[PDB]
Amino acid sequence: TSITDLYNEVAKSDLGLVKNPLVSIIMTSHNTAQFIEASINSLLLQTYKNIEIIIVDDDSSDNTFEIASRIANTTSKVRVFRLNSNLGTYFAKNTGILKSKGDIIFFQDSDDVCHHERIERCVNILLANKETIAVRCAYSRLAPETQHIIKVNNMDYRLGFITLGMHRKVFQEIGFFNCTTKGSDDEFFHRIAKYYGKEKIKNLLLPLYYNTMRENSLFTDMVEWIDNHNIIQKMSDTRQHYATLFQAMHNETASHDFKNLFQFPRIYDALPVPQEMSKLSNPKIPVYINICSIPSRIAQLRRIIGILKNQCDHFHIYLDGYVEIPDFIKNLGNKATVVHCKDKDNSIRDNGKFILLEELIEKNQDGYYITCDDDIIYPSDYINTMIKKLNEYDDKAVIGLHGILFPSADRLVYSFYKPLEKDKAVNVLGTGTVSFRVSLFNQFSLSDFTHSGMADIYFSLLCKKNNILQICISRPANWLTEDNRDSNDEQQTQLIMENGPWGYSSIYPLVKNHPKFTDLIP
Ligand SMILES: O=c1ccn([C@@H]2O[C@H](COP(=O)(O)OP(=O)(O)O)[C@@H](O)[C@H]2O)c(=O)[nH]1
Ligand SMILES: O=c1ccn([C@@H]2O[C@H](COP(=O)(O)OP(=O)(O)O)[C@@H](O)[C@H]2O)c(=O)[nH]1
Ligand SMILES: [Mn+2]
Ligand SMILES: [Mn+2]
Ligand code: NA
Ligand code: NA
Ligand code: NA
C-alpha cells in the first residue's frame, strides 16, 4: 500500500467538498532543513485559498530558519519566527498561535506533507454545524524513500491529533498547549472534549495527512517494528505516566479553570513531569521583572505586561507621571508592586528599575532580577532564554542584549534588535535588556545612583566594582524590537572618564581567569 492508494481513497470520497474565513496553519521546526520546504509547499498548494502559514523555528542548529526566511520572501502567505532557545514543539506552537491572525487554526509539522484538499474538506466539515468546535482527519506514516504506508497497529490510516482544526476561541476558553516536549497534543484533544463535549469534535475519516517516518523523531519511543510495513505504537512509561496525570487532572479540575492552569507564555511546568518531558527553564528561585514607564508609552506597556505577566513571579512597576493606574496593571493584583510617582521633582526615572534590588538584598532574598523598558517588544521565549543563558555561565555573570564596548564615535554598539552570533563580553549593557542573579551582590544602596537618566552606566560600575562580567548574548535579528512610536552627555562623560579603565582592559582580567569565559573575547 502506497501514498497513491491514499490519494485514491480521497478521490473516491466527496466528504467536505460541498460548502471563507482566514485559516492559520501553525508549523514548528527543529533541525528539519531537509524537509521543511516540501512541507510548506504542500500547504501553499491547498485548494482552500484564504490561508496564512505560521512557522516558528525552535532554535535549530542547521539552516532550517534560513530556508523558511527565504520562502517567506517569495510569498506573503508565509510568516516566520525563531525562538532563541530550544523549548519544544508545544512552546513553539503556542508562540505561533499568538502570532497568527486566522479565525480557524490548523497545524502541520515541518517534516510532513498533506493532501491539497485537507484544509478545504476539514473546514467545510467544521463549519457544517455551528455547534462544532473542532475537526480532525486521519494520518498515515510513510516511508520517505518509497512512500509506502507503514501501518500503525494494523491500520493504513487512523485519526490523529496533528490533524486537528478548531475555532480560534478555543485557546481563550481553555488555554494553550501544555509546554512539554511530547504528549500534549493528546492532552489538548482531551481538554477540548472535556470542556466542549466530545460530540462537538467531528472526525473526517479520510487519509489527508502524511507523517514522514524517520529515525529519532519525537514518537519513536513508542515504536516497535514488526516488519517493513508494520509498527506497533504503544506509550512509553514516561508517556503513560503523563497520560495518567493529565487524565486525573481533567477529572479533578473545573473545566473553566483550564484557562488559568495552561496560560502562555510560561516559565514553570504546569503539570509535574520529568526533565525528559520539559525544556522550560523552571527556575529554582523567583523571577522579578522590573520596569519604568512614562504615560506616552501606555500602549507599549500594555503589550509588555501582556507578554511578560506569566513569565515571572512578581512585577515591580515604577509609573512615572501616569495619572491613573491602567486596568491592565490593576488586574495583576498583588502580583505587582506599583510605585506611583506624581511629582517629577521626586522622580528617579530609570533608576526605578533598581528599587526592588535594594529591598531584596536588605531582606537576603534571592532571585532572577530582570530589568525592562517600556519601548521594547519582548518575545514569548524571553525569560526562559535569559535564565537558560545565565545558567550556562553558572549564574556568575550579568547578561543582556543591548551592549556597548568603549575604547563616542569609537564606541561599538550591539543594538538589541540586531543579530549577534556568539556571546561577547562588553563594558555597558542597556538595562532594558538585563538579567542577573540577585545574590551576585551582597550590598546595594540605590542612593549611590546619584543622578537619574544614567542607570546603564551606574549599573555597569556596580558590576565593575564587584568583579562581575557583563555578557552580550547571542540572538537572531529582531528577536527583540523597538517600539518608540514617536515617544548633553556631560554627566555621563564625567562619570565614564572618572571610572576607568574601560575597553578590553576592564574585561580581559575577568575573562582570562575562568574557563567558561574564554570565548567572550577575540
Ligand atoms: O525540540 C523540538 C523537537 C521537535 N520539533 C518539531 O515538532 C514537530 C514534531 O516532531 P516530530 O516530527 O519528531 O514528531 P513525530 O514525527 O515523531 O510524530 C516537527 O515539526 C519537529 O521539527 C520542535 O519544534 N522542537
Ligand atoms: O523621565 C523619564 C524617562 C524615562 N523613563 C523610563 O526609563 C527607561 C529608559 O527610557 P528611554 O527609553 O527614553 O531611554 P533610552 O532607551 O533612550 O536610553 C524607560 O523604561 C522609560 O519609561 C522614566 O521613567 N522617566
Ligand atoms: Mn514528524
Ligand atoms: Mn529606549
Ligand atoms: Na543538526
Ligand atoms: Na488519548
Ligand atoms: Na526544565
Image (cartoon, grey):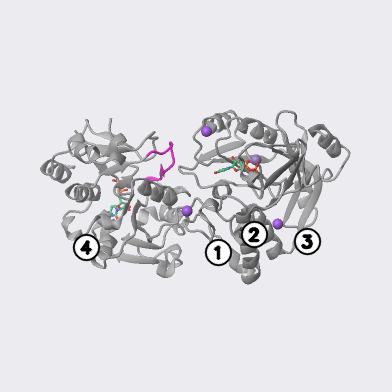
What's the residue type where badge 4 is placed?
Answer: Asn
Q: Mark 2 points at which residue?
A: 243
Label 4 sits on residue: 346
Indicate which disc residue 276 carries.
Answer: none
Please tell me whether mark 1 or mark 2 is closer to you in this view.
2
Q: Earlier in the sequence, mark 1 or mark 2?
A: 2
> What distance separates the C-alpha of mark 3 from that of mark 4?
61 Å
Q: How far apart are the alpha carbons under marks 1 and 2?
A: 17 Å
Q: Which residue is drawn at 40% across and 45% down?
A: 483
Q: What residue type is labelled 1?
A: Leu
CB within 8 Å, label 2 to label 4: no
Q: Badge 4 local density, few (<14 within 10 Å), some, or many (20+)? A: few
Residue at 43 percent across and 69 percent down: it is 333
- For marks 3 and 2, give the one nearer the viewer: 2
Span highlighted in magenta in the image: 474-486
> Which secondary structure type mostly characterizes the magenta part of the structure?
loop
Please, what is the three-letter code of the amino acid marked with disc 2? Answer: Ala
Residue to which mark 1 is pinned: 261
The mark found on residue 199 in the picture is 3
Mark 2, ligand 6, within 8 Å: the answer is: yes
**Distance of label 2 from label 4 (alpha carbons):** 56 Å
Q: How far apart are marks 3 and 2 (CA)?
A: 21 Å
Q: Does the magenta stretch include residue 478?
A: yes
